Length: 409
Ligand SMILES: Cc1cc2nc3c(=O)[nH]c(=O)nc-3n(C[C@H](O)[C@H](O)[C@H](O)COP(=O)(O)OP(=O)(O)OC[C@H]3O[C@@H](n4cnc5c(N)ncnc54)[C@H](O)[C@@H]3O)c2cc1C
Image 1: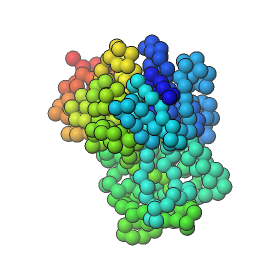
Image 2: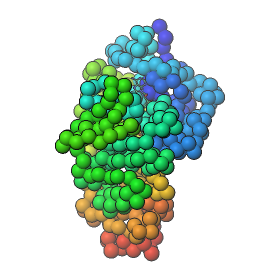
Image 3: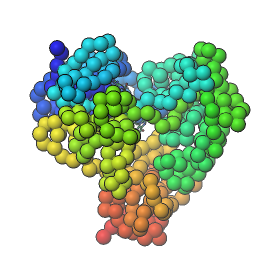
Image 4: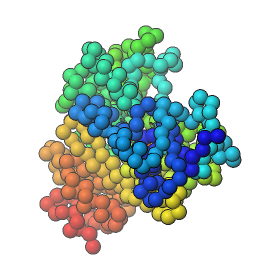
C-alpha cells in the first residue's frame, strides 16, 4: 500500500505553502500532494488580474518552479482527486479507486462555484475564473469574438473580472443583488467609489438586481434569466458569488463544522491527525471578536499552512496573524488590513475624487480595519493601529495631513 508521512490534498495556495512550510521547519518524512488540476501549484489572484489580461505567463504565476519541488522532496499526484477518507484506518481513497495511507493529513481543497444553469447542465462559456484552464477558455472565447459579458456578483472577483473584460473592449454588465457592490466586505464609501469608477469605465452596473438562472442553447450560454423575469443576453457569464467549501468527504467521515470544516488554532479538525487549511476551514478569529469565520484569502491560506506544518513538526505556534487582503481593478490598487465586518463607524481619510484615499473602520471607538485605495502608507501604518485596537478620535483619523503612526499612544 502506497503511504506517505504527510498527505496534502489540494495543490493550491494552502497545499503548496503547506509543503514549503513542512520542509522549512525541518520535516523529513515523505510528503505527497494530490491535486485535481493538471499543472503544478500556481497563484490564483492573477486569474482575474494580470494572467487574464495577458501581462503574465503561466511560468510567472507558479508558486514555485518545477525544480523546487524536486529539491524539497515534495511528491505530487496531479490530475487526481481524493474522493473519500477513512480517518480510523488513516486512509484516503482516490478518484481511480486506489488508496493512499497517511500519518497526518492536510485538507487544502478550497471551494467550488455554485451551479446556476436553468436546466442544470454545464454551459460554455460560463466561468468562475477559478482555474488556469477556465481562464484560458475565456481568453480563447474572447479572441474568437465573444462580446457580451454578464458578471454575477459585486464582490472583488466580480469587479476585477469586469475590469479586465473592459480592457478586452467587450460589453460588461455587472449584477449585484445587494443594495451595493462589496456589501459583505466594505463600507458605503468604498462601494460608491468603485460603482462610480466602474460605470465611468463603461460597465453597466446594476444593484438590487436579482437573478434566476443561466440560459443556454444546450451547448453554450445565451442569456441570464432574471427573477423579474427578464432575460439579459450574454455570450460570457462570470460567476462571482459565494463558493462552496470542498469539504464533503470530511463531513461524511464525521468531521464537525457548519460552514466548511471547523479547526482549532493549530488547524486541527475534529478528526484525529487531519488538518484543514485555506478557504475550506472555519476558525475562531481574534479580529472577529472570537467568532468562527471562514476567511478566503492568500494571507489566510499561507498562515494556516504555516500553523499546520509547525504543529506537524512538533514546534506549534498558534495562528494569530492579522488578516489582510488586496484587489487590483483598473489603475486602482486596494490594500485592506483587519476585518471591517460589524464596524459601527467608517471614517473617510482623504478625498475619493483624487482616487487615492483610505477608510478607517471603528467599532466601539477602536480601529478594526482599513481600506486603502492607492494609499500604501496608510495600509502599512494602519496595521499597527488595527493590532493595537487603537482608540483614536475619528476627528484625528480623518486628517490625511497627519500620518497614522503619529496617532498611537
Ligand atoms: C479569481 C480569483 C482571484 C483571487 N484574488 C485574490 C486576491 O487578489 N487576494 C487574495 O488574498 N485572495 C484572492 N483570491 C482568493 C485566494 O486565491 C484563495 O483564498 C486561495 O486560493 C485559498 O487557498 P486554498 O488552498 O484553500 O484554495 P485553492 O488555492 O483554490 O486550492 C484548492 C485546490 O484544491 C483542489 N481540489 C479541490 N477538491 C479536491 C479534491 N477532492 N482532491 C484534490 N484536490 C482538490 C482544487 O482544484 C484547487 O486547485 C482569489 C481567488 C480567485 C478565484
